[PDB]
Amino acid sequence: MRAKWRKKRTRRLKRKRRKVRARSK
Amino acid sequence: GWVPVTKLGRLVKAGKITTIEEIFLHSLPVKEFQIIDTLLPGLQDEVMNIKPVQKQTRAGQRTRFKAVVVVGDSNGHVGLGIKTAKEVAGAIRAGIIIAKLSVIPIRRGYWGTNLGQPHSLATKTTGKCGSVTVRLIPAPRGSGIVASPAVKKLLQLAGVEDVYTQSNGKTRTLENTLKAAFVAIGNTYGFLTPNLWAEQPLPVSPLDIYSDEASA
Amino acid sequence: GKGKPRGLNSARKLRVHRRNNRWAENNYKKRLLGTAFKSSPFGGSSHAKGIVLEKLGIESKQPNSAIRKCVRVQLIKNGKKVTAFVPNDGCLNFVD
Amino acid sequence: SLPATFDLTPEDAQLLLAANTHLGARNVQVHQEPYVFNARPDGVHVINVGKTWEKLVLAARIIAAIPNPEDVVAISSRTFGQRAVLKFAAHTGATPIAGRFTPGSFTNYITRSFKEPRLVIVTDPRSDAQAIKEASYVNIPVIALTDLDSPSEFVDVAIPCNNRGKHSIGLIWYLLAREVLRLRGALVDRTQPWSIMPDLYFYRDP
Amino acid sequence: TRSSVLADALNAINNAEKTGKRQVLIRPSSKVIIKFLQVMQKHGYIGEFEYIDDHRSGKIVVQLNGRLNKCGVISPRFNVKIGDIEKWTANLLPARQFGYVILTTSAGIMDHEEARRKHVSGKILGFVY
Amino acid sequence: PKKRASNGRNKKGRGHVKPVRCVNCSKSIPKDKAIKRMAIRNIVEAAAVRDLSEASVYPEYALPKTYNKLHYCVSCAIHARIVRVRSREDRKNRAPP
Amino acid sequence: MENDKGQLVELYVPRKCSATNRIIKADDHASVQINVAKVDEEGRAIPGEYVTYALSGYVRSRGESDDSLNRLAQNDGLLKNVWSYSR
Amino acid sequence: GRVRTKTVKRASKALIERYYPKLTLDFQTNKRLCDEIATIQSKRLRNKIAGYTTHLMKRIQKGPVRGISFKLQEEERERKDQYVPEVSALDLSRLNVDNQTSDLVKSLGLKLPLSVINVSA
Amino acid sequence: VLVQDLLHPTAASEARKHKLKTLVQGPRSYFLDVKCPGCLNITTVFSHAQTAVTCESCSTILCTPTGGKAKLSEGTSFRRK
RNA sequence: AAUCCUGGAUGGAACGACGAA
RNA sequence: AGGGGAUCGAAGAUGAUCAGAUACCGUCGUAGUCUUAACCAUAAACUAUGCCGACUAGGGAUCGGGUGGUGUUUUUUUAAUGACCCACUCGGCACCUUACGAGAAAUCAAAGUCUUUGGGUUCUGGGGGGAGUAUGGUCGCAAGGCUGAAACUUAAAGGAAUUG
Ligand SMILES: [Mg+2]
Ligand SMILES: [Mg+2]
Ligand SMILES: [Mg+2]
Ligand SMILES: [Mg+2]
Ligand SMILES: [Mg+2]
Ligand SMILES: [Mg+2]
Ligand SMILES: [Mg+2]
Ligand SMILES: [Mg+2]
Ligand SMILES: [Mg+2]
Ligand SMILES: [Mg+2]
Ligand SMILES: [Mg+2]
Ligand SMILES: [Mg+2]
Ligand SMILES: [Mg+2]
Ligand SMILES: [Mg+2]
Ligand SMILES: [Mg+2]
């Protein structure tokens, strides 16, 4: 796939993980 | 019969030129391998490898075989010839021809202590063809040829007894290794050293001496 | 000037640049992190004794078709499980 | 050295300055040419005709040195020099090649134009660059008639002239043949004028 | 910036003689350049040379023959002991028969065979062949 | 690899050129990578000029001209049978016909 | 060169360019051997009396053979004011 | 189409190269001597050859033809080649030379007439 | 050109070259002695002066500067020194 | 003897194919 | 966060096209587009070419400055100017041609002077993935940035050219 969009996917998943971890922290 | 069509071929067949050293000294261009098998009958050929090469078409692939041939008498002279042809035997034949055409001489020299009958090279030499650098370093007696098999065979057919080597690059391309080694030993006489500083009188060409028994 | 310093009092720079560019390798890294010892179900030993649990019929990878007659093995010293191969024709009938 | 009879005569100077050989190319100047004398207004250069004469005599010495004169070769693919080279070849041996050169005439031993020369002579190296190139492959010297912007690579003796002109080319070829014959001994009288005209070696549009 | 002048001098010489020029102009004329060229002259590698005295640093014009293949400089001027000499020569000379490694000693700038004879060593400068 | 040394354009010493718009597809292309043409034309045509001169008061007049400068993007210039495509050796030919 | 007791070895002592003193190799096919005829007292050329000049493919390719031959000719005497040392 | 091949063209060129003072612009007689002077297996090829010889003779009768060279032609060529005027234009008609050429002559140290004409931008 | 004498070049070339890139760098400028009308009292003046030089007896003016050589006032007489 | 002249364009839809060699 | 907010216009709404079309096309249209004060600290931020310095082939054009010329034109025929021409020069954006050279080649007057390997210095890389990921720090209002693994996985990924 396009590296730009793969990057966009990583950024979204990072955001997801950051907040679902803030749920505990 | 030969039937030369060359000033040099005519002179050779007439017997005026008896040594390839005159050819080399006057930088004469050779075009008939008959000259070389006349002057240096005592050389041996050797085929290094046959690899096939292919060209793609509407209908499959025409494969024609490449051949790398090394000729030499083991006193001071070698040649290298590469030829592609539809059949291996024709490749080898025409490659022997080309190798005889590409014959050059070698400057054997001593590692030190000029005792007897040079065994090594007089200088370090490199040769490049492609990615491949091939270096030849002088070596003492008895060391033999410290090199790969094919390069060893080239040098044995050159008459080198003891020599060291250093390569670099994709040496698994044997055509390029051998062209590099060939250049590296051709540059021996291209290198100037103090035993060659002394001036000479610039001799005259056979093409200017025996010109009457030349072309017509 | 071919990059790297050449001066006569510049050996420190060269030392440290070597160290970092050694970390770029695989052997040095594997050797100094101790992956043999912290991981790699052995302890960097050559062999290991283990306890059979089951036999397996692992299928081969393409391009090929076969069943390779492996076994699951629980090491004695670590307890770790590992799949291991039984090399020969018919030798699975000895590892019951 | 020379006996000083070969030095430039005012008759030859009249010929050269009538044919405007001295009038070289413009301030375009290849720095491999110090033959210039005092660049003119109009953006034009003047050539040292004395140096032209000396180089011409040297070229004639080299041509006379050849044992077999048929080993010398004259090239001219320019229209303005074909007649010149052919008359040169008539009054000497000088196996000529006028017009097209047929690549592979010095190499390619089976070819029908196969010459094995000891020397070649060229009107314009730019227009005849194939010939000098092939000479480089096979150990041949090259004589050329240059102007002051010409590509003198792979060029031995060069004769500065006005190759743009019709009369300059023919004049230089005529003088070359004259000197060569005087050196060979056909023309026993050095001071004599050699009854052949210079306008014989010229181009004619019909 | 301009760090070592001998290097620029010798690069100029090598490029000139690559091109086939029988002369070359050197700047800015160090003492060490003079003694280096004296060595190469004594062994016949260049010919004459002439030092031009502007009051700044000097120029040098070196007449050349085709006898010289490579004049180089070793930067940094490594310190060299009396077996390290043969190590060096084996590394950077074409043969054991000719070529001279040059090295500043306390006994002047000179070549390595002369150094063997005087039994002294020092700091390498360059090489010539 | 590098198809062109100019890379497409005429930017040597600039950094930025402040683009323009293709008059066919409104694409923002730099002024130097574009293709500038100038459509200098007579206002009417070769045909109707005779009718116009016949029906014109103020004889001898001028037939003035319409001048408009055209920029096209690469894609539109190649679609519209302009700079179309060339061989590797003739790409270097920089003069017009 | 030569071995312990005279007895020359190193076949093929080669030629050297008259303009650079670089060796001319066997495959340097742009190398040329100009031969210039001598003259004697009348204006005629002597057959078999040459002034030789070797030139290498390097010098010829770089375009300097003309000047090199000019200066060599004047150093050998067969020319006059054409070439100048001080450009 | 009616294009002819290199066999025809080369054969016709040879027949014209060495039988010009002969066959004329008429296909019939040209045919009836070409069958005699060359051996040809086919009447059709013969007639094609003869037609092209006729066309080439038609070409020759109004100017020359490239590629052709027969005895009469080359003789006329050399006869015109040796043309010379009796004035030999290099000979003097009265000479002009710029001041640069003038002091060139002076530096060479020679005796010549000079009708100096000044040339400026 | 492959042979030349860089020690004895031509004066034409050395005047053609930049003042720094000659064999021995030196100035292409010069000095003048100038007469003002009236007060003779000749005044010594540089070519590339940079200043509106003026005679001490009467402030007439001798030169006005430029990016290079100064422009001498039209009523004056200069001699090169 | 009469006699004024030219160069120039776009224009819809059309998905997919087991691997092995 | 204020201001301004005409055009265009991520979002969104619609008309069509399409097997579907929350895409291309059309019509609207918020944020943005502009500015002020303050954050961000990225880019194919590219000449994908680190800076300083020396040397090495030809050729012409051009930008800026300067020198010279009884050079041309305009002034007040005339001066000084200015604009042009010629020659030269320092410095700059570049360009053309050739390869003595280099390079895997494409190509390069630098990508040359590097196995005949060393002018000085900084930075980066070490098969491809995983992964610029996880974790931990630090900066940031945030968006995110800088720093940055391992497990596991694999024999080829890839560059340049060749003929189809
Ligand atoms: Mg390796
Ligand atoms: Mg230090
Ligand atoms: Mg940018
Ligand atoms: Mg599907
Ligand atoms: Mg599918
Ligand atoms: Mg970045
Ligand atoms: Mg980058
Ligand atoms: Mg630099
Ligand atoms: Mg300027
Ligand atoms: Mg400039
Ligand atoms: Mg600029
Ligand atoms: Mg690695
Ligand atoms: Mg990796
Ligand atoms: Mg596999
Ligand atoms: Mg590719």
Image: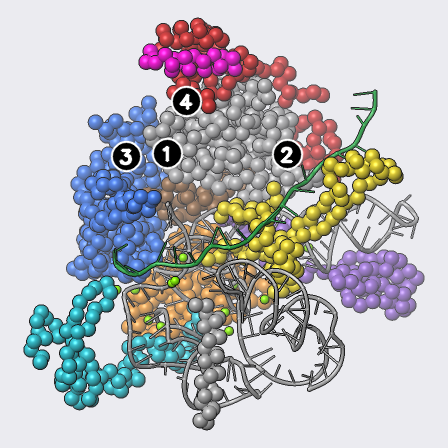
Chain colours: B blue, C cyan, E orange, F yellow, G brown, H red, I purple, J green
**In the depicted structure, whether residue B113 falls above or below residue C66:** above
Q: Main secondary structure of the magenta part?
A: helix
To the question of a shared chain for discs 4 and 3, the answer is: no
Q: Are marks 4 and 3 in contact (CB under 8 Å)?
A: no
Q: What is the distance, in whole Å, between disc 2 and disc 4 at their CAs? A: 51 Å
| Amino acid type, label 4 | Thr
Residue position for label 2? D23
**In the depicted structure, whether residue G9 falls above or below residue H6:** below
- In the foreground, B203 or F75: F75
What kind of element bears circle 2? strand
Sooner in the amino-acid sequence: mark 2 or mark 1: 2
Q: Chain of mark 4?
A: H
What kind of element bears circle 3? loop
Tell me if G63 is positioned left or right of E121 in this view. Answer: right
| Amino acid type, label 2 | Leu
Image quarter for residue H88?
top right
Residue position for label 4? H5
To the question of a shared chain for discs 2 and 1, the answer is: yes
| Amino acid type, label 3 | Glu
Q: Chain of mark 3?
A: B
Residue position for label 1? D107
10 Å neighbourhood of mark 2: few (<14), some, or many (≥20)?
A: many
At 40% from the left and 48% from the top, the residue drawn is: G21
- In the foreground, F8 or B119: F8
Residue position for label 3? B32
Q: Position of residue B3 (x, y in %)?
A: 25, 27
